[PDB]
Amino acid sequence: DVPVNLYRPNAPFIGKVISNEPLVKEGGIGIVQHIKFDLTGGNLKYIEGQSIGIIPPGVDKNGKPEKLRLYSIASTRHGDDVDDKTISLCVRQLEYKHPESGETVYGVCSTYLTHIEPGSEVKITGPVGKEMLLPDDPEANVIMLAGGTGITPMRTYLWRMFKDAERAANPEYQFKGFSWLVFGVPTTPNILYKEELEEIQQKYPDNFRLTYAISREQKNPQGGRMYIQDRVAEHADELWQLIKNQKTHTYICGPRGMEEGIDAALSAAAAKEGVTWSDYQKDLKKAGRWHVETS
Ligand SMILES: Cc1cc2nc3c(=O)[nH]c(=O)nc-3n(C[C@H](O)[C@H](O)[C@H](O)COP(=O)(O)OP(=O)(O)OC[C@H]3O[C@@H](n4cnc5c(N)ncnc54)[C@H](O)[C@@H]3O)c2cc1C
């Protein structure tokens, strides 16, 4: 049923880049690109919440061929043009500084991807993943907690739920539940897909709530910069109330370490009603309603 490993690294699908467009607006920090690939000529199918592998060219410092890196699929199963012909990724160029070994260091696969030109051939594997799947139930509530390119699987959910062309293509999934995205980025220019997220909220104000945590522009009640964990604490009681519904699913995606502050906030909320969140959470994970994908 769920497609998985239609292509493997020993014999990857050779897709072609259609487009590579910037998602960070001027005045933003770093580079994050929306890259769409042509899947025609192969049989790669996928669903929302999954990832694919990309194998970059070249060898590592020991002369060994580079291995795949996994990237969350940014598009629904139908692709951005709703034609079942493409797949998209949302890729941040990894950059960081050493203890002054050279200067700035640039990630191999992400630099390759963010600078890739239309027409180029790319080695793709997958899809992979069954832990970030969206429920078929159109009355489900969906909480989405995303930092940075943790937005990526959330885009697949929200596009499937709310894009006109998706609704026309998916007669079986006409979303009427409530979805709430809490999205943490450093600046307004860094709000990936800002325009479309805000278009969705304006069209569906009773079915989609959009909350930002913008660290360089906002401060929490303690005076520190605003992070997603702060917004979760701010809305902890409300989020807990929603989580108690048997049909509510929560999705967490982004940097490993974002989970700690989220659990602390929800633990304080749940404790007010005599519930130990860590235990309730274990039951949710077992039931397939607590979805985490961080690294
Ligand atoms: C399931 C999954 C989904 C993912 N989805 C996405 C996605 O949608 N978008 C996206 O942009 N990324 C995503 N990632 C991350 C992605 O897989 C790559 O790891 C990332 O793009 C960097 O790879 P790279 O080849 O550019 O860097 P590499 O050449 O592989 O370099 C990475 C290495 O650099 C070092 N390093 C990294 N940061 C620092 C630091 N600050 N200080 C010192 N050393 C450091 C570490 O040793 C690390 O192993 C995902 C990862 C997983 C596991």
Image: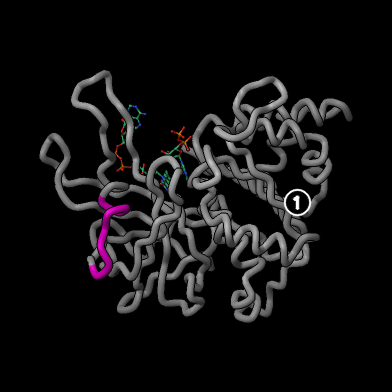
- Tag 1, which secondary structure? strand
- Give 13 or 153, whichever is nearer the viewer: 153
99 sits to left or right of 161: left
Which residue was labeled with disc 1?
248
Asked if residue 115 is among those painted magenta in the image, a careful observer would answer yes
Residue under the image location 35 percent in, 73 percent down = 39
Q: Residue 190's x, y, as percent?
A: 50, 46
* Residue 19 belongs to the span the image colors magenta: no
Residue at 77%, 41% in the rendered image: 239
Viewer-proximal residue among 257 and 182: 182
Q: Is residue 236 above or below residue 290?
A: above
**Residue 27, quarter of the rendered image:** top left
Three-letter residue code for mark 1: Thr
- Relative to 39, 273 lies left or right: right
- The magenta-colored residue range is 112-119
Q: Residue 71 in the image: x percent, y percent? A: 41, 51
Q: Identify the residue at horizontal 48%, vertical 70% (top origin).
A: 80
Compared to residue 47, the image places residue 115 above or below, namely: above
Q: Is residue 81 visible?
A: yes
Measured from the top left, where is residue 109 in percent x and y? 28, 47
Instruction: Give the main secondary structure of the magenta stretch.
Output: loop
| Picture quadrant where residue 43 is located | bottom left
